[PDB]
Length: 350
Image 1 (cartoon, helix red, strand yellow):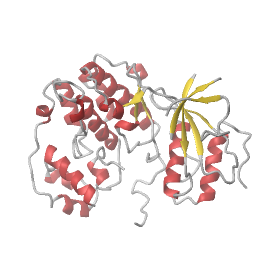
Image 2: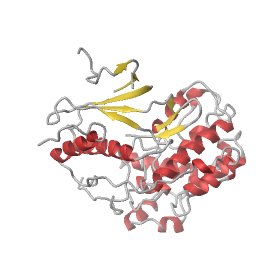
Image 3: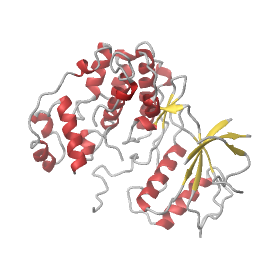
């Protein structure tokens, strides 16, 4: 009735594709997803996003509270997903004219890691961690979201191989599309987020508008180039540990160069913080610090509570092959199945 929010009365819209609302039955966020089926790759990814969230269950991962019954299961092209609301996210936090302590940073970095540990324990690589999908509350609790590019245990390790958007947080192996990805890719991304967290200290960056990401075909080359300008080019040894011969010849074309010392980029931060960051940002995913070593690192001694560092009871198994070219009928059916988890009386499309 004269609204973009074709959702029950039960929810009273308030703020602002996403709105704040009140549930008679707590405050909540409601996301409206337009043009669901126009592009079948974006569609598949929206489906992956919802299906993974629906199956994850942890304090440090955002919760789907409801998916609203479509007016017509056969024809809908829109969706309403009701979500646990958070005060903000890292990206917006960084844009904010405030400064953080090393305790805050440490706390936010720890809660992120804890949530990513759970995710990995459910056999998922997030594969796309970034400030916008690190949700954050005033009490420094952190919730991961946006699993649309994530890789479940069933995703082929060589990649699907299909015949032929910010990249600032992508590990070199991912930029290089090497596949055979490990936990290491998410560790890299967290390292990149760590650099922005450290820039929240007055003595590292003076004015908030100067804050930015550490590493800002053509797009991939400048991204690798910027990574090399700061950390240096890799060892012959480390080039050799790349999976694919073609990538090796390509990385050997970039002129050999020394790295800068990252400590001199964050001179107000403690040695523990820098040591950790240096260990997250290493080129060879084999030598990169693991998540569990991260949680055990002395930087978190004051904030650690090992009991919240829980694992999944089992791996997430999606009822479809999301690495495959799903057509629209398969996508509509799968969506409705997801919607049946909240409204099981809903008819399936015929």
